[PDB]
Image (spheres, helix red, strand yellow):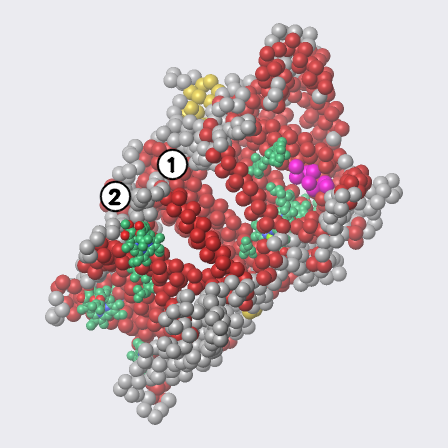
Amino acid sequence: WVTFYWHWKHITLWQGNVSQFNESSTYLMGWLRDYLWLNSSQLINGYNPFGMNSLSVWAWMFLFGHLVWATGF
Amino acid sequence: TVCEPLGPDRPVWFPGTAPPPWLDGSLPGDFGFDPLGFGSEPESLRWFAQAELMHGRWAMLAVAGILIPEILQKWGFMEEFSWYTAGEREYFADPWTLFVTQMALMGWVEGRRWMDYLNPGSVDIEPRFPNRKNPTPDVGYPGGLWFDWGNWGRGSPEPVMVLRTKEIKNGRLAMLAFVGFWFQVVYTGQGPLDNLFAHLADPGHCNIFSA
Amino acid sequence: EVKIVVDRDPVKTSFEEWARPGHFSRTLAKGPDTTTWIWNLHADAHDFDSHTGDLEEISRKVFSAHFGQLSIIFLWLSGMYFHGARFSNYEAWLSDPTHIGPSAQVVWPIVGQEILNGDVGGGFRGIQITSGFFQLWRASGITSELQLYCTAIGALVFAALMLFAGWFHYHKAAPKLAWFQDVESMLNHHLAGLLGLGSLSWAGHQIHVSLPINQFLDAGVDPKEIPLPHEFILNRDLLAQLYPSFAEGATPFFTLNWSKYAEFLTFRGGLDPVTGGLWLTDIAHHHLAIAILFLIAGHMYRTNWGIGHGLKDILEAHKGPFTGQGHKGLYEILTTSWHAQLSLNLAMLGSTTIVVAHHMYSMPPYPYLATDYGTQLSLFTHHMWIGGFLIVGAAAHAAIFMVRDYDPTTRYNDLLDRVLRHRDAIISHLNWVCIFLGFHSFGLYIHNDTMSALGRPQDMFSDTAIQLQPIFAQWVQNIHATAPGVTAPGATTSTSLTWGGGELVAVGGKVALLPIPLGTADFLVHHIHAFTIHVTVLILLKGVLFARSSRLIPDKANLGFRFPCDGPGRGGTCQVSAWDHVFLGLFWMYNAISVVIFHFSWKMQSDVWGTISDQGVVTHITGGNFAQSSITINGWLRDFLWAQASQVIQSYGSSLSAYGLFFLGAHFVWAFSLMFLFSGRGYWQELIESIVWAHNKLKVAPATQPRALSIIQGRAVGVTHYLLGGIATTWAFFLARIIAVG
Amino acid sequence: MRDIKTYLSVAPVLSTLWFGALAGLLIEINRLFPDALSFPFF
Amino acid sequence: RQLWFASKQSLTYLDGTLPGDFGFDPLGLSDPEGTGGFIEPRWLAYGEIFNGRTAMMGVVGMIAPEALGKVGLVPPETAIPWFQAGAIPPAGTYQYWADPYTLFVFEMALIGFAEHRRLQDWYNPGSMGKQYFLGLEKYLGGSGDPAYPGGPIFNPLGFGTKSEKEMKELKLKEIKNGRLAMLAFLGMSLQAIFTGVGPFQNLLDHLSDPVNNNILTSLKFH
Ligand code: CLA
Ligand SMILES: CC1=C(/C=C/C(C)=C\C=C\C(C)=C\C=C\C=C(C)/C=C/C=C(C)/C=C/C2=C(C)CCCC2(C)C)C(C)(C)CCC1
């Protein structure tokens, strides 16, 4: 939670649009939409049937996480 | 106090049937009709008896107030129009003032009566000059020359249970009459005498099934 | 022989007990010394077999319970028909069903939820529905709110009647044993009586009411001046105008020249372009032939007369060399233990629900059904879920039977004995098959994803790379597309259109069905389905076969069906009861259903559904990226899971906004489940202890001594919350997405 | 009769009726005071 | 006991208790292992009696008006088949001395009075001769058995003089005439549902022309 808060705050400040944070950070759907959904769109397209990118590893590693975690269950 | 146990003295509301045992028939107007057995226990029985008497008396007053002015409109001098629409009739004062005054006074009275029910004889209005012994009570029949000045509820004019039977029967009938009048005005748009005459003219067709 | 023997008035309708909870259980009736009493009360209410020892009383009780269930179902149907009558736009929908959204629920304007009553067209405002009643009410020619109203009334009447019947049959005239235990006449009737005559009377209602009014509506008329149904049977001349043959009374039938009726009873097949649905003539021929089949089937077993078989006279004959004595005595097992019957029937009912789910989409029976996307999708997935739940229940009750009422001394069998005699071989081989399928059906996805993220696409598993071809499926599709040529001359087209041959059916600029090709992605998804099903079967079959006694605990059965463990001894013995086997298998069934429904949604929205241009070019709702993006899990994230989750997440401030809100609560509960699934009890017991102290300090310590839930109830509440979260999440996702885009 | 009274005094039904009455009170207040954010009395 | 299509479950309870037992019951309903309410053999005899009597009255009455209209002096204002009298709206109607519906509910209430009292007698025999009934009390005790009430209200002329044999004859006659009237009523109604012209006119037909034989046509029409 702490790191979510810090990262969203800074990722808004760096783009100069802290206004968006202040507006749509008070309703959870705002967090799921403006913070996770959108900011993940550069990642999940790391590798597609049209090739790959520098981001490939992370995308791969990303999925890796969402697997190992599940195995814990 | 006369009892009406089973037998010929007990004309059963449903011929050929033994009435519920806890329906003795003491209360005038009894015929052994309680298939739901709500009168199972005595406290509920007396409570429902009081409710029945009150409903009957209020229904008599209500049906009189419906009937008489409408017929005195139809043929009499003054024309009292639709009683169901008299609820919204316009008077000197607003309906809410009337409502709150009604509620105040009726709360006073019915609360005194409520305490009399919960505690018989403890709340009564019957003066006592010396050496003349007053009457008791039978709640639902206060007695004394405040509500019985004709000396009818005590003996001479008729054995009591018979007159109370008359009262309860007419009260049930008046309850039916009130609910009928109201339901008719829900369906039709006239008074009771109008429906009556419409039925008289065309008994064969002018009915509920006329449409 | 068989007679009408019953008994008179066992239990009186006296409220003496309602004020005393747990009258049935001797221990429960004593009093709640602690708080676990009020859990244990609900926990064993319906447990009839633990309340007596004779089957007569529990049979009477279940006979009454069935009436309770039927009363609830009738009340539900009545509510549905009412809300259709007094609160829908059904008439406007009938006016033109091409682009008018079925809505059958309005919300009171109190707390800002007016936005819920979104724009649905036709001068109406209301929460859009996807139940799909409207296609039915247009099939049955309701076409008037009076009909819905009176049908709701009649349903209420039947509900009260069934409730009465229940009360009367349990309290006053209780059936006896030789009635219940008499299954021959029950089979005889239910075969001949219920199903057959049912389909027959429905064929009646279709050929004499639906068919003409539906044909008229297809011709195109305002249903106001459409002739009423009874005015189509009283005066013959209308149907005469429609169907010449139909003006010949009953001579062509009785005189065996049935071909005259060929017009309204036929065998066309295919779909009807006017509505994409089925040719109602075909469905009428179907229902009628099925009625005749059930009637001729019903006459098997001897009941009172001298003809007919006996269900004891059929089994014992079958006795093969390997198995030995065969099914001897099995008739007694399946007649002396309710749980056995419950398991068998639940299994068959779940399978039938699944096959109904399947056959629905590929052969839309109703009219204007294959073009109301959300309705088709929601129906299919609902039926799938119901089937899964029924199957799991079947396995659980089979295990319960295995524990309690199985015994070789009197309820003997020589078949089940053999089966149990080699359980280890069964479980071992099924386990190995499960490992094999898991590897060669998921590791393929893993390999494909990895070789994608490593810039080696030409070493992938697809059509454009190392290739796997589902050849048997395409073979069967070719056969089904060339069968109406020679094998089935009496038909006109293929049995459905999804077979790989023919043209496409499109109504109102949208397509309804067309051929369906299978790519390597389909091979992979089919093997995923096979693997997950095999694993669920492994779990549940192991539970059943080992409910009696395992090589770990020697006398498991004596410890009962549902108990938490056998202590931490011998290295730990957690979750050994069959009940816990079902607790486990539930999650795997959930996973199977979830992946199946996701696959269905993607395949439909990527290869069938969509719109058709004026010229005839098709642009599917998602662009047809299945065969190139279903082969990478990262793809599933990107192309399908992330992308098609838009419409639910922007849904705030619109009509669909409700579908948005659930999308969080669904997740939330989903979380919450873990709190119960992961923790234990002793910790919570100590915490409750300290809280009781904190209260007792203030003279507030309640006599209903607080107690953290028992272990089994903890697992139960956990699994319930988890299933709720998952199913609600997929529900909100599906509805929002499909009803927004489609 | 008294049996049905003691049954009616069992916590489920009593709680259901109590909660129904409370919810009705709250929704009626909301009706008669839409959106009611502040305390604009003092 | 002239055996016509009997069985053994019939003879389990049909031991000859009903006046003139013929032995015809393949199904075996009233087997007394568990006595089904309203499947009681007493109730069965009661039902056959009551049904046959009602059928006698109905077969007389439904056919009476039009038939009499033939060469009689009941006017052609009612020359209408029983199934066209008005009971079957898809056939005909008539303007009466009331409206249709209220008439029906009124006659329903009257028949309900009568049959409710009769049923109450059935449960408790003789128990109608206790309550006030504005007279009529000293008659409704009956002759003991609700099957056969007797009483000068229902025994005016006086038969079964000093006898049970005469009662047996008269009574066999009862069962036979009840069954015959049942058959005739059912046949009139089936012709009506399939012929469509009316029974008495069907006699008008079948007096001269033999070739009718309308089972050959089997024409099913309103
Ligand atoms: C004392 C009882 C009583 C009496 C005498 C009447 C009399 C009448 N009603 Mg009525 N009614 C009653 C009770 C009664 N009603 C009740 C309780 C209801 C509520 C369901 C109604 C609802 C009602 C409607 C909706 C309408 C009438 C109408 C009428 C009139 C035409 C008859 C008709 O079609 O309705 C027949 C009435 C009924 C079927 C109601 C059945 C209930 C009663 C109690 C039947 C029982 C009979 C009674 C107990 C025995 C007689 C007692 C006593 C009079 C001797 C007629 C004057 C019509 C009208 O306005 O006239 C033009 C009309 O449209 N009634
Ligand atoms: C107001 C209130 C509050 C709070 C509350 C809350 C916070 C809640 C939450 C909640 C959440 C946070 C979430 C939730 C969720 C829910 C859900 C989720 C539900 C569901 C239900 C249902 C019923 C469903 C159903 C279904 C589906 C959909 C699927 C399957 C099918 C069916 C139909 C079954 C407080 C405390 C302040 C106070 C008290 C009151």
Picture disc at residue C238? 2
Vertical order, C65 against C597 (above or below):
below
Q: Chain of mark 2?
A: C
Query: What SS does tag 2 mark?
Result: helix
Q: Chain of mark 1?
A: C
Q: Quadrant of residue A34?
A: top right
Q: Does the magenta portion include D20?
A: no
Residue B9 lies, in percent from the top left, at 43, 79
Q: Does the magenta portion include C718?
A: yes
Dot 2 or dot 1, earlier in sequence: 1
Is disc 1 surrounded by few (<14), some (14 to 19) or many (20+) residues within 10 Å? many
Answer whether residue C424 is visible to the viewer in this image. no
Vertical order, E115 against C457 (above or below):
below
Please report the residue visible at 39 percent of the width from the left and 41 percent of the height from the top: C86
Q: Quadrant of residue E207?
A: bottom left
Residue C679 lies, in percent from the top left, at 77, 36
* Magenta span dominant secondary structure: helix
Is disc 2 surrounded by few (<14), some (14 to 19) or many (20+) residues within 10 Å? some
Q: Quadrant of residue B197?
A: bottom left
Please report the residue visible at 34 percent of the width from the left and 39 percent of the height from the top: C143
Type of amino acid at the residue the image marks with label 1: Tyr
Please report the residue visible at 46 percent of the width from the left and 44 percent of the height from the top: C79
Type of amino acid at the residue the image marks with label 2: Leu
User: Bounds of the magenta span?
Assistant: C714-721
Picture disc at residue C417? none
Residue B28 lies, in percent from the top left, at 43, 71
Please report the residue visible at 29 percent of the width from the left and 67 percent of the height from the top: E185
Query: How many numbered discs?
Result: 2
